[PDB]
Image: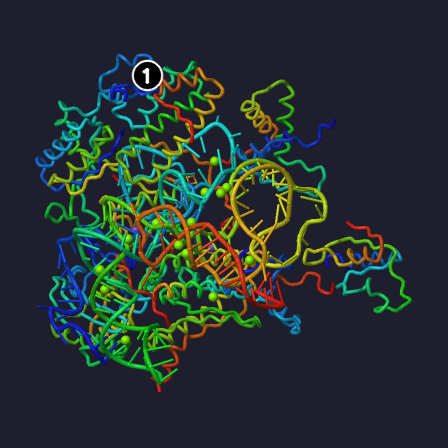
Amino acid sequence: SNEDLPISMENPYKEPLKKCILCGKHVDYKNVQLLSQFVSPFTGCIYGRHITGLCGKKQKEITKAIKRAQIMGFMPVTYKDPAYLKDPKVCNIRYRE
Amino acid sequence: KNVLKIRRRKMNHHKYRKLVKKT
Amino acid sequence: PRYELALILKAMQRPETAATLKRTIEALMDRGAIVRDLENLGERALPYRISAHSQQHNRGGYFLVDFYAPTAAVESMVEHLSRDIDVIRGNIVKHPLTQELKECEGIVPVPLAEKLYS
Amino acid sequence: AKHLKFIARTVMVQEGNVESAYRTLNRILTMDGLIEDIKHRRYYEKPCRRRQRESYERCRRIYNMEMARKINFLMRKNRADPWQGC
Amino acid sequence: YHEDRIRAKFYSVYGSGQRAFDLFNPNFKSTCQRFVEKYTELQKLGETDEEKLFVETGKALLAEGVILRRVG
Amino acid sequence: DPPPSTLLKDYQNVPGIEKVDDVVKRLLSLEMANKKEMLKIKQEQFMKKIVANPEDTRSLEARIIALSVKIRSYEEHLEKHRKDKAHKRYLLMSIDQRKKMLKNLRNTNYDVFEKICWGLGIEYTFPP
Amino acid sequence: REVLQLQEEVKNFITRENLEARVEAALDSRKNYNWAITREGLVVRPQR
Amino acid sequence: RQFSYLIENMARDCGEYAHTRYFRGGMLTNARLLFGPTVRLPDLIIFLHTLNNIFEPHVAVRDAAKMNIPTVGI
Amino acid sequence: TKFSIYPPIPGEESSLRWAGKKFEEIPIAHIKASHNNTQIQVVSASNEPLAFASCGTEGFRNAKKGTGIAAQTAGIAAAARAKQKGVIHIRVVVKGLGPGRLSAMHGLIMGGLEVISITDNTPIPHXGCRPRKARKL
Amino acid sequence: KVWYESPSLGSHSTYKPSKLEFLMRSTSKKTRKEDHARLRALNGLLYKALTDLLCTPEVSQELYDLNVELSKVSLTPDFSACRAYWKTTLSAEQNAHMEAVLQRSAAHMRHLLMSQQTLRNVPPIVFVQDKGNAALAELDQL
RNA sequence: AAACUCCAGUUGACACAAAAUAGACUACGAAAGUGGCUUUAACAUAUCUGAACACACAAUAGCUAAGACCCAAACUGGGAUUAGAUACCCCACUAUGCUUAGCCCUAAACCUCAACAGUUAAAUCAACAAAACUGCUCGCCAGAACACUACGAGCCACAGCUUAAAACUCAAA
Ligand code: FES
Ligand SMILES: [K+]
Ligand SMILES: [K+]
Ligand SMILES: [Mg+2]
Ligand SMILES: [Mg+2]
Ligand SMILES: [Mg+2]
Ligand SMILES: [Mg+2]
Ligand SMILES: [Mg+2]
Ligand SMILES: [Mg+2]
Ligand SMILES: [Mg+2]
Ligand SMILES: [Mg+2]
Ligand SMILES: [Mg+2]
Ligand SMILES: [Mg+2]
Ligand SMILES: [Mg+2]
Ligand SMILES: [Mg+2]
Ligand SMILES: [Mg+2]
Ligand SMILES: [Mg+2]
Ligand SMILES: [Mg+2]
Ligand SMILES: [Mg+2]
Ligand SMILES: [Mg+2]
């Protein structure tokens, strides 16, 4: 018929879907350094996904990892271990003065 | 909706339970 | 199946720490376990004070034992660890490396209408 | 009780300014939800009541975020009238 | 269009040209369009591989004086 | 039950499994696996014993054998968990579903219905 | 392939004969499972 | 309103009529009252834009159909 | 060096000092700010009591105990008895959201004590005892 | 939508809160129930914008050290000024220093709100001390 | 006000009670329910529909027996309020909430939406709720009130549950 007519196919310019900082990485309860990045420095409270930026799957793994590490003797509950206060700040929360 | 039908049933059941209690 | 024993031992000198590990690995073998590896995570301060066997602990030796055992061995091993006075806290979990992580394309957007609707 | 002390919920005072240190501590406890948690725990909230308020709070937050997004989007045209007189 | 596949790869590999689109000129040709036309010419010469047909096209334009700065 | 030394259904037909170290044989046996792996061996044992084509899993016979293995697992579960109402429901539902299968197999293929009853030890009962 | 890989690993598995050697060989070593993530998704291994 | 001035001039040039302003309720359906009993309404209404400034249909589209006036519209 | 709101960690080597004393050696002012009272106890780093004052021990009674000015007065009283024992710098540990939570700290300062840190230790159970039923008002 | 109604017929209409619109607005017009919601939401954004500017060190090192906290922020519906209530500290002298720093900063703050162009058309920002502790300051001085 | 004053504060030891944050998530389960950790077992059906009663379950409250008991808490007692206060407010304490073994079988047990399959074109549609419908099957309904009642029958239920009328009365509900 006509060569210039549109052709059916999938979007070639489509961009990849977004990925969380932990997409594709194993979350172990023994890696307290990683887990400590998602708890409050002052209170030890686990941050919600709106603060951590994690997806539902990794938000769940982090939560389950923290709870396991805390009661198994690897991670404190009421505060962030001070050793990990100088690690990269990956959470969208501003606290001090 | 209003609870006027429930209120009729409520009083009927209260008075029945009280009647059974007395006798 | 394949399990991982997270073992926190009483802070002791090298001879008594080795005797505790040997006594603990033999208990696994006596129950039919095939021990794969033993890892030392180092002695550290506990995240909180732990009372075990009429003693208070602030430091402990963290060790891992990767092993295979029948499903009935877990219950019997947990009981053995509860009676060893040199073990502060011992937990047996399914080895994390057995569970294979499923691939993720990314974060699909969720319609806000569903949020309030749900 | 079994944890180390003077780490959790601890703020240092700078240059003797205790008012600013107290405001920082109160801001920390507020953002982490401890202040609201303490208050809701003075009397027992019954499970049906907790679910109702949690459901009300989640729907109000969504409605406010969606109403903020709409105004931000519709404020782009708040510029001066380009066709005044027409 | 079939050429959209070539445009997606060109933008990924080389990015958008520092040259500015002039959508007022109805006969404007961008660096990507110049790349697509050469890519189409070489395909008609019998070459059928995709990864090979893309590398030869970049060389041809460099010979013609075109600036192709790879993004990464 | 199959012996604990029995190899897993996946590793039984790999070439050279009989010449590996004893430790490797223990790690590929039922002893080192969960109970669900023992049930896959039981199902395959009944399939070869009863059905004409042991690889046809969509036939009414294979479904009766597969469900009969699940039913036996629930019975063993409930022998140790007598207040588990969730699995008691699953058992009673599974028995009802098998009876429906047996009813449909009896009506369509009686010779196969008889072999399923003999092989699995099922005494078919007509409903009241 | 899984039986072959597993057959080599069994050579390094702990046994009653080599138990003492592996127990002592562990007290001298250290295994670190800690690492941190960045906003760009990059792992930051510990300084050791 | 970007084109109000352009459209008003085009109407004057061709000898026709333009309504680019706020459309008051009943210009067509109540014309005799607003203009007089002998007012002649348009025989053709040409919409260069069929939507009003709240992205709804221009009221004159519905009212032109009510008055049996043919409409041309972009 | 820039100021850190995070307290110095014990066992590490900090340069901060108060009258030649390390953070671990500074006495502690324990403020219990209840809804109907405020209690202040100053103790040494070794848990030796040095001063105690509450709104009740300062002559306040009934609803007057549950006021800021009553807590401020209790702080001044505890500060005076603590200053006599050699206390200048104190670490404040306040538990409770009562009206004397902040006022009790002001009284400690007006009494001659210098607060170097503030710690909240308000008890929050993580799941714990059931509180009393809601009030109908 | 939610139990809170959001079916507005003129939903797409461009919200234009400017001082000039009020003078051309019809006072005869009666505000809709949802007309307040648009104003209430804008006030929430102005609160978040000022509150965030306050806690960032760079904007003004004087401002950050003060650790100012805003009690409430209600823009005037007239659009003349953006009221910005700031909680008053108990220290009597500190309420003057904080107030003085705020007044000087306020002039620069308005330009910095134009950096966030969505909030560009912001009226002159006005800071109000919370009389709860401030009113008592005047009396105790006398 | 009463109450306590072997009381309170700090520190240490310390549960058969309850499970911050995560959770702004919306998952699991037939429903009821299920949100600390670990492990074991484990989540029926290769066409659907199919029971007041068969089969198996079923929050809270409650019963029988033996235990635990921090805290909460009907009832009860005391304080106060009030014209009265068998309430609302304060304090104390019990049954009870927990465990074990049996019962009991109810709920605004409610997305107030029966199961399955299909459609988005017709008229979009009484109203509101939750856009409007088709096929097919089971269950159920036929003015109000009498009536979650009477009688009968069944039931570990005995002041109970399930099923469930009639007479008199009204022109509404
Ligand atoms: S986006 Fe892939 S795991 Fe989070
Ligand atoms: K919990
Ligand atoms: K409901
Ligand atoms: Mg009645
Ligand atoms: Mg059915
Ligand atoms: Mg039924
Ligand atoms: Mg029936
Ligand atoms: Mg019933
Ligand atoms: Mg029940
Ligand atoms: Mg009970
Ligand atoms: Mg009590
Ligand atoms: Mg009384
Ligand atoms: Mg009791
Ligand atoms: Mg319990
Ligand atoms: Mg319910
Ligand atoms: Mg049905
Ligand atoms: Mg009737
Ligand atoms: Mg009833
Ligand atoms: Mg009855
Ligand atoms: Mg009867």
Specify whether residue E2 is in view: yes
In the image, is residue J44 above or below residue A47? below
Q: Dot 1 falls on which chain?
A: F
Q: Secondary structure at mark 1?
A: loop
Name, please, the residue furthest toward the right: H38
Q: Residue I5's image quarter?
A: bottom left
Using the rendered image of the protein, determine whether residue D17 is visible from the camera's viewpoint.
Answer: no
**Residue A22 x/y as whole percent:** 38, 41
- Of residue J24 and residue A29, the one placed in the foreground of this image is A29
Local packing at callout 1 (Cα closer than 10 Å; few below 14, some 14-19, many 20+) is some
Q: At 55% across and 22% down in the image, what residue appears?
A: E52
Apparent side of residue I129 relative to residue D69 in the rendered image (left or right): left
The C terminus of chain D appears in which quarter of the rendering?
bottom right
Tell me where residue K115 appears, x and y as whole percent. 51, 40
The residue drawn where x is 18% and y is 47% is C45
- In this view of the protein, which residue sits in the foreground, C44 or K137? K137
- The residue that label 1 is drawn on is F12
Identified at 84% across, 52% down, the residue is H70
K54 shown above or below E37: below
Amino acid type of the residue that numbered disc 1 sits on in the rendered structure: Gln
Number of disc labels:
1
In the image: residue J44, left or right of residue I40: right
For the N terminus of chain D, give its image quadrant. bottom left
Q: Is mark 1 within 8 Å of ligand 1?
A: no
Residue H9 falls in which quadrant of the image? bottom right
